Image (cartoon, rainbow, N blue to C red):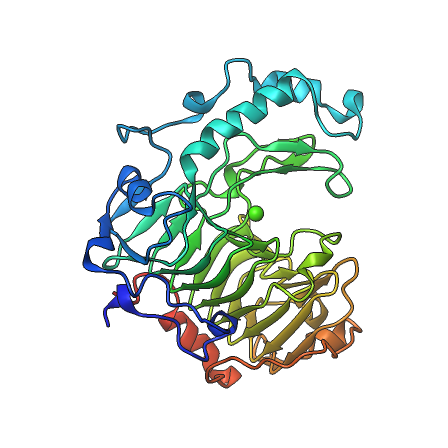
Length: 399
Ligand SMILES: [Ca+2]
């Protein structure tokens, strides 16, 4: 079977549960498309009711910030006539506005501006769909694929720079507030039976180091790479290359979303994380199997310094096996970050800078996450992870 007709193996992670992930492998010849621009992609996907098995091949670079004539769109094209960053900054300055959500004219103008961009860059993927990169250079630039459906396969594509021109100021976010942006490369919002494999995710030609600071906080134009929220379940993410980005993957969006308990069953294996700051992943509630992943970075990088790998959030149940972390000078405890409600973590075979460590025990956590993985392929010895992952992870390694 060619790349477009391949399906997820019957034991390959949580994605293989029940009906498994076959994407659009059963598509008839008339539902097999090759797309090379935004117009073709949107037409091939159709609406949310287009559940007919379909295979979409991406050829070349697809820029999502383009109009209907495929001409580039910049900040001014999306900007509401009444929006002005200078006026917005003056209006919501914490010294005069205080710590409360922005409201009024400038925030309304900012929100309208953001909705203009959202209409072009966010695309919903319908059920029973396989989207694969043709050849070695398939790319999606600026777009945010949203998956709310069942049975979707995304492979061999490089996703770059899901950039938000109008970040929202949120003074109540954290201790000193933060600027929040809306687009990920891939957003799994209630989606089920998904396989993301051999993809590459990065911030393209607009790294966060080029962003200014307003109110003492970075003016962040990016959000996540592969995030999962609102009951997403039965997902396998394998052989992906995540690099040069801040917040990579958040599974479970809120401590109050107790409906996520029993869901967010995600398997992450053979992924490469290079120069990723945090959230790799940051989990709430889910039974997440993390194995054979390779993490590399530096705490003194000038662009994307390592902060932590695994985020232990409320009721998270990370089961980690044979993962390798290469961050010179890092202490064993700082491989992870423990958040509100995070009490347990099971990790075995963890290597930090070639040394066997126990991340859970270094943070005084419980090792009882209460479950044991049932769906997984062969687990590589920790000593072989770095080579296997560097050589095989990312887009352009298959075709
Ligand atoms: Ca997100």
